[PDB]
View 1 (spheres, rainbow over the protein chains, first blue to last red):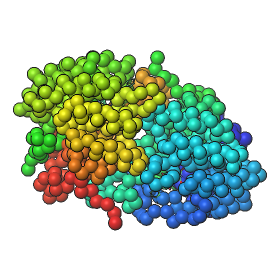
View 2: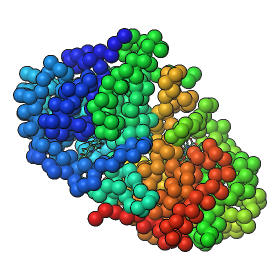
View 3: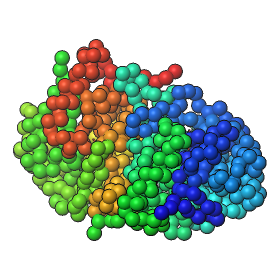
Length: 313
Length: 313
Ligand SMILES: Cc1cc2nc3c(=O)[nH]c(=O)nc-3n(C[C@H](O)[C@H](O)[C@H](O)COP(=O)(O)O)c2cc1C
Ligand SMILES: Cc1cc2nc3c(=O)[nH]c(=O)nc-3n(C[C@H](O)[C@H](O)[C@H](O)COP(=O)(O)O)c2cc1C
Ligand SMILES: O=C(O)c1[nH]c(=O)[nH]c(=O)c1CCc1ccc(-c2ccccc2)cc1
Ligand SMILES: O=C(O)c1[nH]c(=O)[nH]c(=O)c1CCc1ccc(-c2ccccc2)cc1
């Protein structure tokens, strides 16, 4: 019985990794994730210049999940590139580097300089599409023409397999359109579904107040709130992108939640809110819990059940 | 202390009502909702002809909420119009009638017939904008040019104050565009935020199967999953539509949750999933709970706190 996976010309001890943004901003964070039992790690989505991000409080968690408007605080691309090129121990596990430039030219400049390190050291690029374009327009992955532009330019500049982090969609016609855009780009080898559910609002009844400061308390939701939305997106893209991998992210707190993602079609399974709340010990628990479900069902490997969710009649 | 209010030239004993689709499809359902302690009731969204809806199972509920792909089963518009015209006791509470035709023409046909009954009896129209659109396009409320058309054609056909039932939005640019469309129409006097969060997917780990039969298990989410989304949309539209009322719907299971909707800006609070699960006795519990929270806080009226959610600096 084993959780091993071999994909994208790498080997993974198990499918679990951090979600981008969680436990991955500093060298300390990345060393911590490397020391953990996760099968991989991803760095904080970065910009060319360092960013302080939004005013605090900017993250809060509750029994059913979290809300955030971090504002892309990060140490800048040069830091993350140095981590990938000089500091990371690739004999421990694979590394993904997430980018989130504020324009197509910023992403193009970063991927140009990432390429040789990707080719020499094997770092993998995750391009965050659920991200800021021109203010007053929707995030990039909610603007299908912008999404296409970003993918064309990054595919030309980078020239190597990469993947994309996608916001959730809610309408079948959007699933259709988004997957069709992705399927234009053969270098898009993985699709991570999903980023936070955008612009939720948590209010504290005792204080009659929102709980985060930026954007009058509006921010992206994660955790238990979003698991059915996450599953829907993983399965939608799994069915529509037969030549790509899907990585699942959203609502994973247990091996059972991970099993559901994998039934929906997930290859790797990323953990955000629950990892932020529990810490990196979560990965030993998730491994154990997933193995127990496999043992009860007689499954020996992940491929035996990946994407095998049954439908009714 | 009592929760009575006046809106839309009607008096309401309290702000609570069923959410469209729940406990409102048949004469028996409507008589049960009328008998309840709710302040108002809304009928099942209807089409010109009766519909059987989708194959069962098509609704399932869980600790965190529900999923449905009912497919608009309903008795047909002639039934709901007769209920509004001849059967409903207006001395007990106001009635809203929800329409969801499969084209703009179908809606215009139904509203031209509802107008005289609205004049004579005071039934109120809720137009469901989660309705069918042209080939390749998303639901009407997610296609702003189609929404503008529907509202223009219904406003002209109907000629009286009405409201609209909106799906959730997840992007601040979308809130800005949708509210601007709605503010083009002075007869749109109330906005109900929100319909179900579209196309989630619930999977049972034991059986490795989706839990509803239509659409390969994909359907709209309601209940605890969607409270922060519902609050965000209520407040976004409350902020953007100062000459309209906002009705809140989504995730109400307690007086506390109702309280949060009202702080966000809700004038009426609709109850879907938790009403489906608990039955119409929920209305007395929600009233008691809301009045208890008001008493502890020293609030004597809903107006004292409606829309008064606090932001941080
Ligand atoms: C504090 C915080 C920071 C995040 N920052 C990023 C980021 O930099 N890039 C990104 O792609 N997603 C980011 N996300 C989204 C997560 O990667 C993940 O998609 C989302 O939280 C849902 O997973 P969950 O339900 O396990 O939290 C962030 C989430 C949180 C909570
Ligand atoms: C079984 C079922 C049927 C519904 N049918 C309708 C409908 O006919 N018209 C409509 O506007 N919304 C319909 N909805 C959506 C609800 O009115 C409500 O917007 C949604 O369930 C979110 O509220 P909740 O969190 O209280 O469930 C339906 C919901 C359920 C669960
Ligand atoms: O850094 C984040 O806030 C973030 N949080 C998420 O849940 N997912 C993400 O992908 C990111 C990074 C993308 C992002 C999100 C929000 C902003 C933002 C929000 C409010 C005001 C200013 C910036 C900028 C970039
Ligand atoms: O009747 C519903 O399914 C329904 N459920 C909701 O949560 N919200 C609604 O507004 C509605 C009625 C709108 C609607 C939703 C789905 C369909 C549908 C779904 C699958 C296949 C055919 C029609 C038709 C109308």
